[PDB]
Length: 148
DNA sequence: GCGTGAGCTAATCTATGTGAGACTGATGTTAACCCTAACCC
Image 1 (cartoon, rainbow, N blue to C red):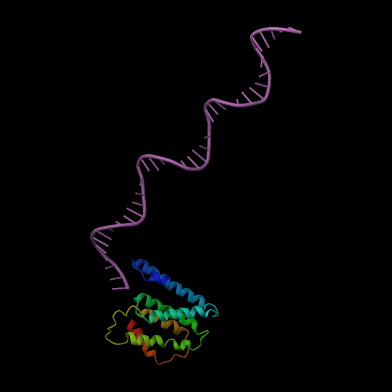
Image 2: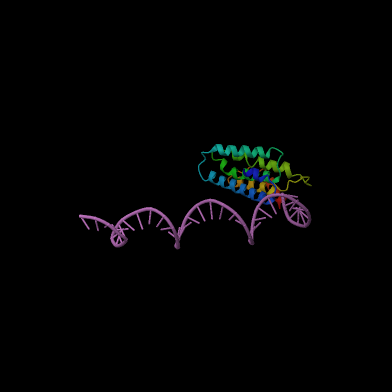
C-alpha cells in the first residue's frame, strides 16, 4: 500500500508517501540489524522486490531511488548469515554507477536524481566492510566528485 | 524529477423548520371514611 501511494498525483501526498516509505524501510532495517538474524525470509523478499523494481523500466525517479536506498540500508545486516555476500555488494552498485553516469558529457536523460541514493547506499555498505577491494576506490572518488 | 495559475465541483454552513425522546406538573378521577332524609320500633 505504501508503494501504491508512492505512485500517485497530488504531489503533497506523493511526498508524504515517499517519506513514510523511507521511514518504514529505515525502521525495519533497524530492527533487522538490532537482533540476530533469524528472519531471513523477510530479507529475501525485500531483496527480490528491490531487484524487481530496479531491473525494469516502469517507474519514475522516486521509486527507483527508494529501492536503491533500501538496498543500501539492508546491505548492512546481510553479512551476518551470508558471509562474502557483502563482498558481492559494494561491487554491483559501483558498476551500476559506472555504466549509468560515469561517461563524460552526460547524456543521462534524467539520471541525476538517483545519485544521492547511490552515495548513501554505498556508504552504508562501506561502514560494515573489511578488506576494501582497493580497485574501485578511484571510481568511488570520481562518483563523489561528480555528485559534488 | 516540479512549481504555478484557472476553472470547477465537492464540501460545507448557517438560518429556519419539524419531529422524536425525556420530563414535569396540574388535574380530575376513583376511592377510604364518615354523615344524613325518614320510620319506626
